[PDB]
Image 1 (cartoon, helix red, strand yellow):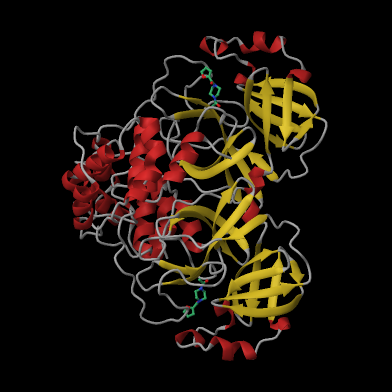
Image 2: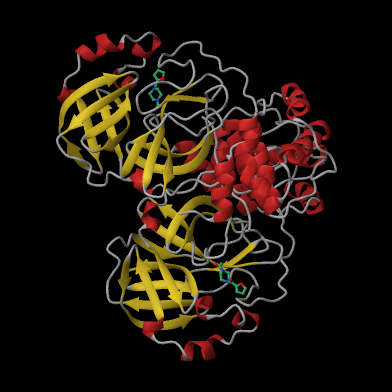
Length: 304
Length: 304
Ligand SMILES: *CC(=O)N1CCN(C(=O)c2ccco2)CC1
Ligand SMILES: *CC(=O)N1CCN(C(=O)c2ccco2)CC1
């Protein structure tokens, strides 16, 4: 029993973190096989980051200008290229700790673990969600860029995020491991405002299911609703529209608990309309939206 | 910027988890050097766990009855002993991945990372606090016993917790790595009720400091208080008494922010008396008490 905001074990990713230094800029890189992946802004002076021309800046850089250090051993860089907003540094040694891995581009509402690193050294691990406005709410100080987000399926690390920037509002923006930003963000120090941070409805429902399974039941009511009726209330409270796809995804949690998805919708509807009245659910005073239906099943079933 | 409930990187502890099987009971064990540490209740039939006599049960057990598996390789058990509520299984092979380590017995209010495991395989990592009633609020299913709690100081893992039991109220009890329970709990399936789960005052204040540092400032007021005046309000709200020791510990966060500890006490006092009025602090609708002053400094400074 008990339900916790739970990250994947980080060891497989710890084994992949290196330090990348270009001139006076030191960031993190991800070493998989004989490639090191890092944010292309490693090549910028903070002056450059006002309006950088990365192709032009990169002409001035050689293999030997990229200093790559794994623990306290230097890797030999034998090639470099830019793919979107990342650099791929070819090194002469395959990472002996390379796990089975994939690069995946997640959808908004999907959750992942971040291994926060500084100078290629892990400081901590936490669970995130790709927000509907394509930001993440992370914990990233200067030096943390190149820290990655991942999921693990048994022995395969799916890398979904690399950290690139903090918006003036203190929320975070980054790329997949092909170097394509999530959302409309650019690796430039300019006016970039996030859109509406809406609540991930399907995740709230999954977490209400988790609460029932773990004995927190006070919010279960006598009501049901329809997708359309629920969605009117969702819209009013800046919740994501609930789709039949979302209902299908919640099917197994529905089955296990014997609470129809639309009944749990009606419970969530009353919580939105009435508030918590100073009560808590799984130790929260607000409705948690950074557990996926998959996360709830995994943690409630004990997958390794 | 941003502040997250952050666990230590788990890799060093992942390398220490094994499976222990005695008859039909399979739990987790911690392999350090040539010793495997596990809960002594590995020897019990669930019938036994009503009123077990562990010394008597252990007479019936040989080295060869303890099946120890590290990945998919069996370890040879060459000795076994009971220390308090843990078994120490001597194996013929030193764990090659043994990190630098210590066994520490933490105080209530101290935080630690848990690596939740099943069958000696890591499923996830989360941050906990030793509650003032010597319980922890974890995420533990059947098979999770022998999962451990730890802190890391650069390269040294301090092991502070091994998971042994769930109370009927779905909160968790366990031992240090000398096998001594935290609090008054016993490894018996009997009536065991937790005392008052009071709020860790010094941790709330540390987290209010974290909030100020990360730009969440709406709750800062024009007031101050005294330790005695604050403590009257603390008592009323089932908060731990604040001591001069706690004030001294918050000194560096006071210094960094320029907010006197007693001013932040007065802010917390108004939050207790007035509530959040539907507002949030670092994305919470309640006052978080599972960050230590040390945790706030570490995460705000980016220690690795
Ligand atoms: C995410 C990260 O580590 N960084 C550090 C490098 N960089 C800057 O310091 C910078 C330059 C101009 C604006 O910010 C980006 C963030
Ligand atoms: C923590 C853990 O893994 N367990 C599993 C073994 N055990 C029981 O199933 C049990 C027997 C009697 C009561 O509970 C303790 C908890």
